[PDB]
Image: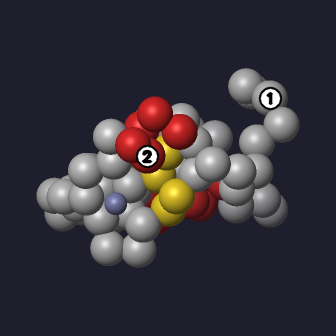
């Protein structure tokens, strides 16, 4: 898990989409992200480089 997580210290950019809860990483925050096709899943934090398998992966999160 990690602990009691919520929007505290974290800046989430709209354009570069970089997100850091670590205050040191906001001081080192460098806006410039080549974000072609990458989708992070909340629980399965490993990023998917494809949209189609991601859609089938959401079907895996869908109940009956
Ligand atoms: Zn940024
Ligand atoms: Zn997932």
Q: Residue 64 carries which label?
A: none
Whole-percent x, y for residue 27 in the image: 39, 43
Q: Residue at x 25, y 58 (%)?
A: 31
Front in this rendered view, residue 45 or 10: 10
Q: Mark 1 points at which residue?
A: 3
Front in this rendered view, residue 17 or 61: 17
Q: In the rendered image, which quarter is residue 3 located in? A: top right
Q: Residue at x 42, y 66 (%)?
A: 13
Quadrant where the N terminus is found in the figure: top right
Q: Name the residue under label 2.
A: 26
Whole-percent x, y for residue 2 in the image: 73, 25
Q: Element type at marker 2?
A: helix
Front in this rendered view, residue 59 or 39: 39
Q: Element type at marker 1?
A: loop
Of label 1 and label 2, which has the lower sequence position?
1
Q: Which residue is drawn at 47% across and 52% down?
A: 19
Quick check: 43 left or right of 28? Answer: right
């Amino acid at each position: 898990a990690g602990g009691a997580a919520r929007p505290l210290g974290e800046f989430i950019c709209q354009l570069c989409k970089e997100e850091y809860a670590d205050p040191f990483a906001l001081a080192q925050h460098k806006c410039s992200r080549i974000v072609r096709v990458e989708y992070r899943c909340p629980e399965c934090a490993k990023v998917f480089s494809c949209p189609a398998n991601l859609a089938s992966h959401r079907r895996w999160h869908k109940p009956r």
